[PDB]
Length: 495
Ligand SMILES: OC[C@H]1O[C@@](CO)(OC[C@H]2O[C@@](CO)(OC[C@H]3O[C@@](CO)(OC[C@H]4O[C@](O)(CO)[C@@H](O)[C@@H]4O)[C@@H](O)[C@@H]3O)[C@@H](O)[C@@H]2O)[C@@H](O)[C@@H]1O
Ligand SMILES: [Zn+2]
Ligand SMILES: [Zn+2]
Picture 1: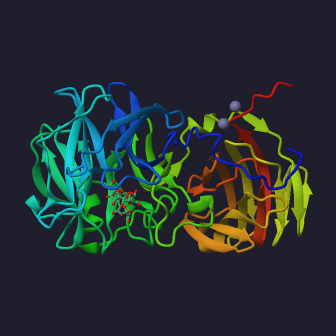
Picture 2 (picture 1 turned 120 degrees about the vertical axis):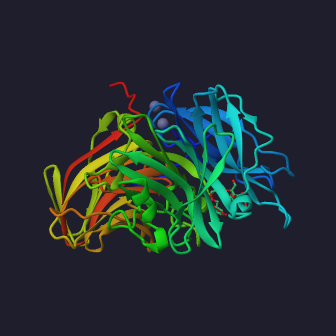
Picture 3 (picture 1 turned 90 degrees about the vertical axis):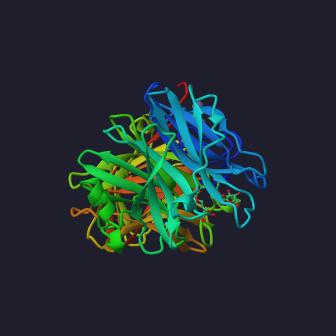
């Protein structure tokens, strides 16, 4: 704690709040509020590095009351045989049927090397009375082309029941080349009728992992954009279901806010929600990086799967959504640590427990631990200033990794700083009029989420942020840093 040199830390210690199974990684999650157990069941596609040919992504599960503590459920729905329709499983959705007291999980069966007459993707279902033993329904095969949709893109079923008792299933597919979310209705979850297109997908986009829900006086669609330049979780909103569906009708592009509904950036994907009646949370995954290299974020798309991340939905008075930390996660960080300056550079002053940094100045703080909570307040002199939050920055580090907050650009960027500096990706968010940024960062080994002013929610993979110093800097203008605090998970030091 008295040195600030770079240390080659690892993820082997283990994750807690941003869950990873002992073997493999967390792919698309399928969260569900279990109304009998009164907790969340998060099914997810289990990823291995490498996966088998043909038979991959079985559905595993974890249980959580709150998004911070997880109990593994192991393998719940296994892959089919190499030649079967669900040789590989894709994402779906779970729902409880009070009439027969069965949990139903609809999923995507991906056929290995389909023939011209076969369907690459078909929706299938499994049921369970207790969420431990699941029985595949060997007679249920929902094919898109039966209803005018696509034979090979027909996936990610989302199930919900409306107040009138009707069950709805939304499926991401195509019709005449264009992306369509198709709707099916049922009284009993067994016999399904097509209700046509729920919503079309903007332009040539494709909305994976759709999720529709009502929260307060607004209806929402949350989705994950497949297009390579986006790869982010986004949403639309409407006061009525018809208003929601109209946001994309005829490519209207009625964005819900001033940032095209982009909730997070490229290190949080496949996000879907569930509510316990008090809060609605969103679960997605944070990708791994090839070679554990924080600056290798994929040439086209990032690696698929990684760690499970939960965030809380914040509904604003105008109906827009931002994401915040789940309250139970904010409580895993218990012992406040001492914050000490280990190095200063450039044009800056230390004034007690505040710091003023001019253009080009940096301050480096003492080493973080393994699971961290970092909080501070930044006041900039102008609404065009720029400052940085840097990790893995040892006094001897040639390069490091930073969240750049660019007020003149209306966004935060994740970048590599120092030698071989390079921009990686960004995250638009509302800039405060009073130039005050209340920052909180929650980390679990290599996974962290940065929150600012209940407006920015920025997940990042930062290998080796643990057990290494962190830093604040000013790139443009002048900033004053206040109320710096750091709290930790491990804290069991008898003194
Ligand atoms: O080729 C197999 C090989 O590819 C990976 C990703 O590198 O898995 C992709 C395949 O998984 C499948 C079935 O499990 O889909 C899973 C779900 O993923 C979703 C959203 O995350 O989208 C699939 C979509 O992901 C891409 O990688 C995006 O470009 C596409 O390849 C693909 O269309 C969701 O919509 C799916 O349900 C299967 O469909 C994918 O091809 C590896 O893990 C795997 O080993
Ligand atoms: Zn401990
Ligand atoms: Zn630990």
